Image (cartoon, rainbow over all chains, first blue to last red; front, side, top):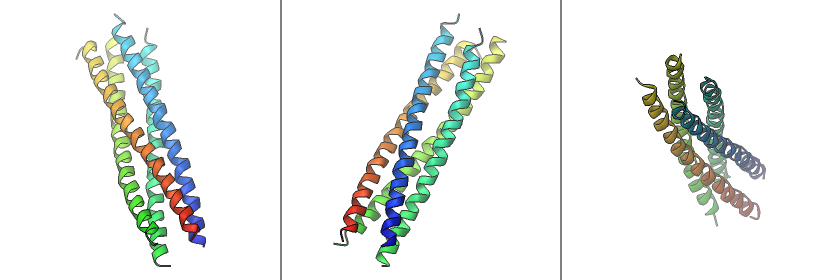
Length: 46
Length: 46
Length: 48
Length: 48
């Protein structure tokens, strides 16, 4: 079937893009942590 | 000095770009889920 | 066994709801980064 | 307000987005696990 071949291509795209979302979310959490280090460095300022 | 705040500004602009990428990529995922149900609907039609 | 199509239909509806939730939370995140940009602007008006 | 109180707003915002950011990450992993069952559905559908 050609619908079954299309479903396989789509399922494979969704996993690739979904891992990319997951990678990018992970990077965002580390950038939120850097903001906590930036905030912590702001009260140690004075 | 004000290298903390300039760094935070670089981080804030970074998170916007990457959170937009997450958002655009999630949006594409939802459109692929609906194509997936159109495939499911095309499978009962076939 | 046309229960795989019933399973596939159950999964696609599940993924759309959970994916819409991801999309709402990301959208909320962007509003908070801009709130963070307003905080950044208030910090330069303060030190300077 | 006071620079000591802007940091409190930034601190509340930073902790909020991290919690919501963890939630996005939780749902994305759950989504990847469903695409896997979606691939198992396709493979069980081609054997038919």
